[PDB]
């Protein structure tokens, strides 16, 4: 397949460059480990108001104040 | 007598051949320069876009703080 690649690179280099760019753009996001970073960056952006919940009495995971240590923090985004 | 004649030794050389000096670099050099420029631009854009995302998050949480009075 080296002869075919050399012939098509000598004849039409534009199509070879386009196909190489397309192949990298297709097979590269499945290899990089930074796609989940984009996922939680997009999910961490506050478009809507964080509507509070009524305190029934047993909710240990949610805080009572935003400065409380419980809750989803973004020190990873500040670090990156 | 006096006429228009060439000198005894003749005139100087006169060129009649195509002269193209072939100035420039090889293809590997320019392609590597372009790839390096692309990588530098991609790195700078990644840094500035991450900073802009953090700034946008800060402005959004400022609006979140200001919402109930409005």
Image: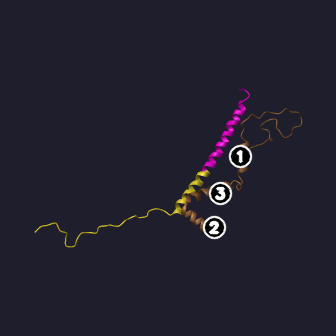
Region in magenta: B44-70
SS at mark 1? helix
Query: Residue at the bottom extreme?
Result: B9
Chain label for disc 2: A
Note whether A64 is above or below A80 in the view shown: above
Where does label 1 land, which residue? A77
Where does label 2 land, which residue? A1
Q: CA distance from mark 2 to mark 3?
A: 17 Å
Q: CA distance from mark 2 to mark 1?
A: 45 Å
Q: Main secondary structure of the magenta part?
A: helix
Q: Looking at the figure, which quarter contains the N terminus of chain A?
A: bottom right
Q: Position of residue A52 (x, y in %)?
A: 80, 33
Give the mark toward the camera: 2 or 3: 2
Dot 1 or dot 3: first in sequence order is 3
Q: Which chain is yellow?
A: B
Q: Is residue A37 magenta?
A: no
């Amino acid at each position: 397949v080296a002869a075919f690649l050399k012939n098509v690179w000598a004849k039409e280099p534009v199509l070879v460059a386009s196909f190489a760019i397309a192949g990298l753009a297709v097979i590269l996001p499945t290899l990089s480990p930074y796609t989940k970073y984009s996922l939680m960056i997009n999910r961490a952006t506050p478009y809507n108001y964080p509507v509070p919940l009524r305190d029934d009495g047993n909710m240990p995971d949610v805080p009572s104040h935003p400065q409380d240590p419980q809750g989803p923090s973004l020190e990873w985004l500040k670090r990156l | 007598v006096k006429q228009d004649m060439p000198p005894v030794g003749g005139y100087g050389p006169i060129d009649y051949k195509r002269n193209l000096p072939r100035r420039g670099l090889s293809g590997y050099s320019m392609f590597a320069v372009g790839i390096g420029a692309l990588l530098f631009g991609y790195w700078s854009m990644m840094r500035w876009n991450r900073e802009r995302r953090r700034l946008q998050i800060e402005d959004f949480e400022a609006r979140i703080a200001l919402m109930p009075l409005l």
